[PDB]
Image (cartoon, coloured by chain):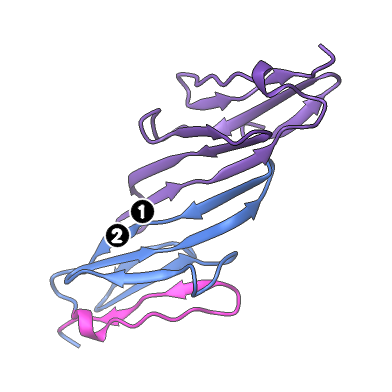
Chain colours: A purple, B blue
Amino acid sequence: GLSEMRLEKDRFSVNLDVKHFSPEELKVKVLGDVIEVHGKHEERQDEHGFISREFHRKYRIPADVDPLTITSSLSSDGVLTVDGPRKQV
Amino acid sequence: GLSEMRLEKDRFSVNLDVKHFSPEELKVKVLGDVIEVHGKHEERQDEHGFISREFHRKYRIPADVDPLTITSSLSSDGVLTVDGPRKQV
């Protein structure tokens, strides 16, 4: 899954779809214990002229996971991985 | 195809995805010979907490199709059909 959120045994990791747009339109934001990855693909040609996929990907941090230990990372394939180990780690 | 634009023999018809959101967030707009169906699904729970699908579905009207003859229609299944016959019709 390249769009899945899951707290592992003792580690919080997330994959996210950023295949067709860029850091410039990918607004990875957080709000305390919140992770709002406001992604966006503008000028998106498809089956009907242009569209856009503007996201508000607001998912929260488990109470047992430290926001500060969570780090995002965007691959060349366009997969944004937001992952921080538990507070226990 | 429920998201396909195609000028038929002599008739312009479009299907569009509006399965998970409503006329209130579905901003069917046009700009002259342009059809910008700025759709939007906010508060969209998925594999990672909430997201949103805010669209800018800007596809243009064939020069042989009358904008005035194009009418949209949203089904109970959440399919928006934007369809107007040619100017020839």
At label 1, which amino acid type do we have?
Ile
Q: Chain of mark 2?
A: B
Residue A38 percent coordinates (x, y):
49, 40
The image shows residue B19 at horizontal and vertical percentages of: 58, 66
Q: How far apart are the alpha carbons under marks 1 and 2?
A: 6 Å
Q: Indicate the secondary structure of the residue bearing disc 2.
A: strand
Instruction: Name the side, left or right, on which B76 lies relative to A4.
Output: left
**B53 displayed left or right of A41:** right
Residue A40: x %, y % from top left:
42, 42
Q: Quadrant of the N terminus of chain A?
A: top right
Above or below for B58 versus B73? above
Residue holding disc 2: B58
Main secondary structure along the magenta-highlighted residues: loop
Residue at 40% x, 69% y: name it: B27
Magenta part of the protein: which range?
B66-87
Q: Residue at x 68, y 44 (%)?
A: B49
Q: Considering only vertical position in the picture, is A46 above or below A85?
A: below
| Type of amino acid under label 2 | Lys
Provide the residue designation for mark 1.
Answer: A51
